Amino acid sequence: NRRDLRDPDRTVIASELVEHSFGVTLDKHVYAALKFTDEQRTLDIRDYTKQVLMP
Amino acid sequence: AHIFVKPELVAEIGVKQLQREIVLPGLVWTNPLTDFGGSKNDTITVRVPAITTA
């Protein structure tokens, strides 16, 4: 603050120290899910690593 | 007057038929597939793999 020098009133405006904050939340669940019948897994899958896991 | 028996001379002096220079074969994907005999209709089917979404 500023006040006039040699001012008849001698009051001072006390300043405030306010700490702020914000929250960071873990709030999402990203997933990839696959369903294979016994026929699909037995007959239609050949590698399962370059055909299921890599995709 | 005088008669002279002369041949007909044929010469080659490097004059050829101007003809294109070939560049296309070297730039195109040639023979990723070979076993066209042994596939119906001389057709080999290429499989493009799958992609999922999460």
Image (tube, coloured by chain):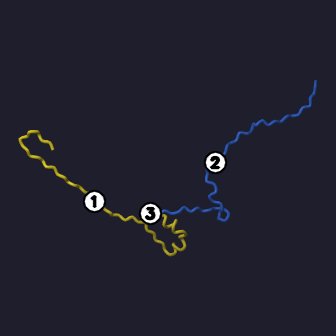
Describe the element under mark 1 as helix, strand or loop.
loop
Residue in view at x 62 percent, y 62 percent: B44
Q: Nearer the viewer, residue A42 or A23?
A: A23
Q: In the rendered image of this protein, does residue A45 appear above or below residue A5?
A: below
Which residue corresponds to the image point at 17% horizontal and 51% vertical from the top-left?
A: A16
Gap in Å between the C-alphas at discs 2 and 1?
62 Å
Is disc 3 placed on a helix, strand or loop? loop
Q: Are marks 3 and 2 on the same chain?
A: yes
Q: Which residue is mark 3?
A: B53
* Shade representing chain B: blue
Q: Dot 3 falls on which chain? A: B
Using a 10 Å C-alpha cutoff, classify the residue at mark 3 as few (fewer than 14 neighbours), some (14 to 19) or many (20 or more): few
Q: Nearer the viewer, residue A23 or A32?
A: A23
User: Mark 3 to mark 1: distance in Å?
Assistant: 30 Å
Image chain in yellow: A
The kind of residue tagged 3 is: Thr
Q: What distance separates the C-alpha of mark 3 from that of mark 2?
A: 39 Å
Which mark, residue B24?
Answer: 2
Q: Nearer the viewer, mark 3 or mark 1?
A: 1
Output the chain of dot 1. Answer: A
Where residue B18 sits, quadrant-wise, is top right
> Which mark, by number, is residue A23?
1
At numbered mark 2, what does the secondary structure look like: helix, strand or loop? helix
Measured as percent of width and height from the top left, residue B35 is found at: 66, 62
Where's the C terminus of chain B, which quadrant?
bottom left
Is label 3 in contact with label 1 (beta carbons under 8 Å)?
no
Subunit of label 2:
B
Q: Amino acid at mark 1?
A: Gly
Residue at 63% across, 54% down = B30
